[PDB]
Image (cartoon, rainbow, N blue to C red):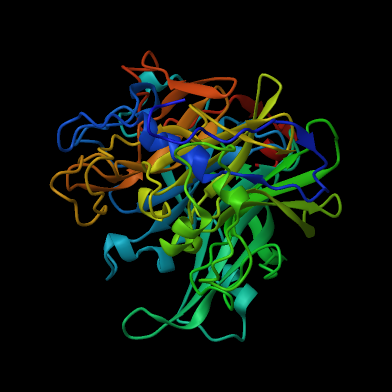
Length: 492
């Protein structure tokens, strides 16, 4: 109830059938709360965010995970409940990787990304390992031809492997199903698409292995298209050449064993630039003195920002086949990007976490790059945005009062840590891993210090007593469960 700003929308948190068609809305009313709690008295380049929603500062002299590989979106090996498993004594993490010494600049790595994996010994406290994580690099995760099979006999200039998840299919076996986003591009000489990009959510099954020294994989030769945008629940390339569709995360319905769901980044279907946002996407409470009109918001171009978090359900046991369901959350007229959705269980509630960019917010809505959060009573809920009704869980240190800039061209009046990290993922215990983007005109293609957020109902707070003032050591992505498979172990 903050002076001069609209009240946040009302959200019940009530569960709905996941098969139903109810979509929660991260409304303008909700999102505007961010600038409502942003301290407007700060000096140029100081953090205007509320201190408990700010991520600790990353040091300029951070280490690198590996001097020979660029590393960003990073996940690890999880079961159907998102618990993180070591395998026969090893921790493993899967990364979008790229090559520093090939021709291209950090910012153009994306059309080049390859999934790689790192490993290190399990069961060891972070204070006892190298400053840079101790991660030894295993190489590419997939055999070289294999991800491009999805686009065999189509024409493109670039085909890359974008992020997703790795699921331990057998809690004490070795089958892993990697879900990832198999993208293709057809760029002209100025990097413009002559033809709209393709993103296809893809499964590949493979087996993990480990001896005493060394981790490795087998399989990953079969890459099965699972989902691609249909242009009716999820926006496609024909509709918007800049459409988002990626970041598959799967899980077993906790209240229903056997049934599997997946959550992924999307956009609200339809042709780009259609000005079809509704009073519901604005979500103001009746007679609020500070509400905006639908006509104002439209006139301002906000209808260009049309993110959703999508849902799909596996149509059998193998996770090789899936049906789209109505989106879980839309952010029409609020933000174009809700990346890396995950459902997360805590205290018998359901949390959707997703990350976003300051510069994908719609006109007149404003917030940091970082992690945004929603709570409810089920998989499909009338989700309540976290903290002051805003959705903000943990932003990079940002002055919201001054211009944002970019991770390659910083504005002088903005904070040098606005782009310190991205791709935050919330691990059991509320531990948050992420990659370093920009710290004081130092680009990091590398893992950021793991950090912690205590989560309490519809609110959160960064734990300033985690590790070292909140900073928990670089690349710390720890396993809370152990897969001890003696029989595949002796099969080396």
